[PDB]
Length: 138
Image (cartoon, rainbow, N blue to C red; front, side):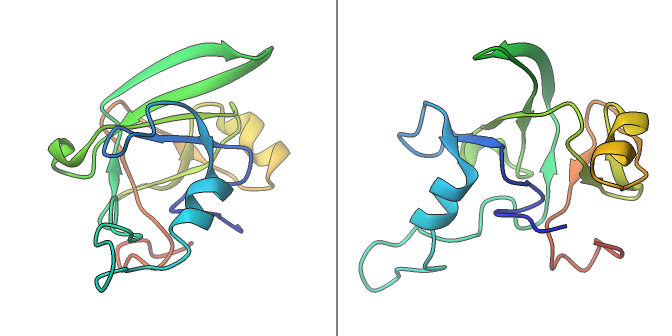
């Protein structure tokens, strides 16, 4: 799949409490902001670093955003003290769950929508990004 950031597709909304981005941004927005993977010379922090090992689902809410039903997951980079990452995505959003592979909340729907047969996730399942050595089949 063509992810914009981490294991997230386009049409996903990002909110890292690590930043002042307390409100909903697009993936393409943060991906664009973090276009440089390090501004060590100017402003350190800008990096595809948050969630480099994985995003562990802490809690989940199913809400309706602007008329669209969404999957809201509060993620953990391992030490959430970096900043809680909250995401509103579609019901058919595939998540590369560690040890399991491509998993989702509505796997029967996910495969119909993205053509990817997915496993059932569980609260506390960590999601891996493309390039992570533990993500065997991304």
